[PDB]
Image 1: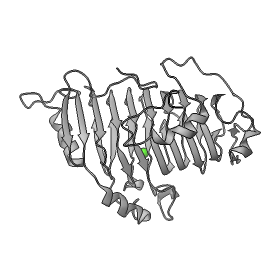
Image 2 (image 1 turned 135 degrees about the vertical axis):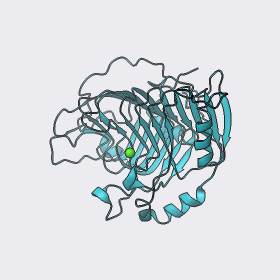
Image 3 (image 1 turned 45 degrees about the vertical axis):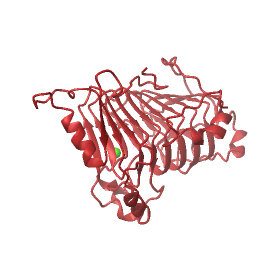
Image 4 (image 1 turned 60 degrees about the vertical axis):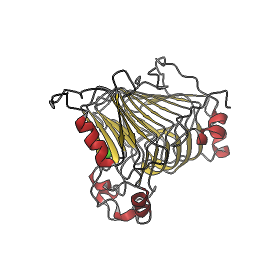
Length: 352
Ligand SMILES: [Ca+2]
């Protein structure tokens, strides 16, 4: 089936007529996709020649580990990323248990793409768009069960004092439907955009069952459109959490926030504040802030914090099927279903 538990509906490359290939390294993936574009006669087929499932078995722990040992030397290096440009036959990049990458995945003008079981860390090229996962002009994409990490730190002397490391899962353009789920994102300062600018508004994104720890902000930095965030575990948010801007609407349901600063907010623009519908989270009222170490701060420009913890607008009926567990259950159970090596295990109320 194609149910992603969110706005995206895709099985990626795991469809009829698909071809399975094993990639032992980054270049192997690049080579496999290149070959997947040619027909029996060596001629290119628009959108790819057939559906593809690429199982990545490479391991770049030495690169990830060396980078972690000298984080400030990363931003000035060349960015590395497997581009998935104009491949629309259906593609899946799934890492084998034990695999790892010190490069990212850049989805662009493609559709029906799935990324699973990929452990991506401490990527080089923060000053040159060295993103872990990027979804650009690509609908029906499912970023599921990955481990995206770096250091939630900003070295000095970096371009715009904001480039030590790039994003975990940036989304932009006509990536009309995307589902980001069961990802273990940690040590990331700038987690993910949902629109690249004030003018890149829209899209319907679902963030569910993601485990965020020690992340500074952008969970996501939402610009217009709809965002349904359910069953996520947000801990140690050092800057801000969901930032709803350019009149976007968010449905924040059954999440667990703890040791978070500005967990739900609308800042940095000074106008066109977005809205949120709160329900079933561990925080039910402002009295729960102290309980879960929830803190709020101000901004130089007009802003709206959920310091009242009340819905500030509405949200259309969620189109897809989804069965969220309780907030307490995500707190208790999520850390073992999210990330790589959980065999793509999903948390159901049965396990609560
Ligand atoms: Ca980026």
